[PDB]
Length: 186
Image 1: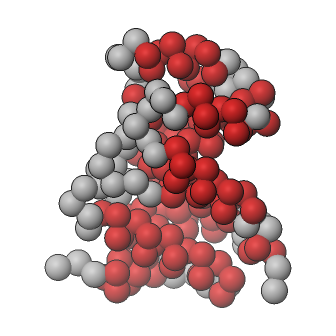
Image 2 (image 1 turned 90 degrees about the horizontal axis):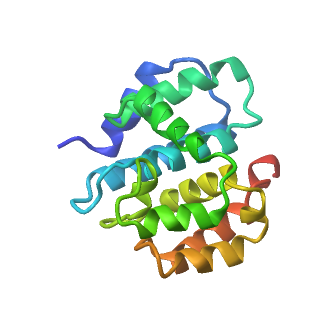
């Protein structure tokens, strides 16, 4: 059975250059989190998870130095998790087709019952991660700027429409947002 230890060894075999301790802590926490999702019988990859992994990684790595290693680290992280970094990157990018839209047009597409991909991945059943909350926030950021300024109102509008558990999303986004600067502190 493949263990977290196997995943970490794969990571360090794929990226051998030094990583500062501050960032090894964040990267290993992410490696563990993804591994534990994959072993969960109720978890199924979707573009919402992809977007969340890419967003979370990009945010904690925004100050990473040496910056030229950041893409190699992402590659290594994905292959260590038996994922394809190019698939995650394309799935994250696929949300950009929603750029500018008001929330009303998104709701209309959900309510049609046959939303396009990747919007359809907001109809999330099976195992929920905080990464899916991160992913939702990144999507909402593509929409009309109104939407994430009034995050409260937006989340409340989504709650009767999608099965993603919006009370856990609120919780997880408050944590994520409140902790943006912690990696820059002692």
